[PDB]
Image (cartoon, coloured by chain):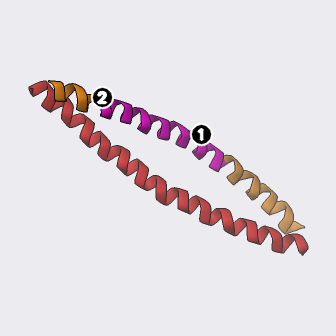
Chain colours: A red, B orange
Amino acid sequence: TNRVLSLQEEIAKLRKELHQTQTEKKTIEEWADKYKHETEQLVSELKEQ
Amino acid sequence: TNRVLSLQEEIAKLRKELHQTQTEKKTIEEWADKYKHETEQLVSELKEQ
């Protein structure tokens, strides 16, 4: 029982932590994709230039 | 103890999966940084052009 309450505290904390990393990584993955939208465009414009 | 053996299996699995994400995240974060190394350079060369 002393063990049963202690892992309930732990199993909650990581299930917030990886949600926080998932929310940040959805931003970073979107941000990397939209920086790809930047990087594909200059290989057109600077080739026109 | 039926509950103890079942979460010992769970508490092992996430300790692999978050490591698997962490190693990939170290790659993406390095990769995004090295596509900042690209991004700083064309805004000098295409400025000179």
Magenta region, residue range: B17-40
As drawn, is B49 to the left or to the right of B40? Answer: left
Pinpoint the chain carrying mark 1.
B
The answer to which of A7 and B48 lies nearer the viewer is B48
Query: Which of the numbered marks, if any, corresponds to residue A23?
Result: none
Label 1 Cα neighbours within 10 Å, binned few <14 / some 14-19 / many ≥20: few
Q: Evaluate whether label 2 is on the same chain as label 1.
A: yes
Residue flagged by tag 1: what amino acid is it?
Thr
Residue tagged 1: B23
As drawn, is A14 to the left or to the right of B9? Answer: left
Residue flagged by tag 2: what amino acid is it?
Gln
Q: Quadrant of residue A9?
A: bottom right
Secondary structure that dominates the magenta span: helix
The relative height of residue A4 versus residue A44 in the rendered view (above or below) is below
Query: Which of the marked residues, 2 or 1, is nearer the chain's N terminus?
Result: 1
Q: Position of residue A2 (x, y in %)?
A: 90, 74
Number of on-image labels: 2
Alpha carbons under labels 2 and 1: distance apart: 28 Å
Pinpoint the chain carrying mark 2.
B
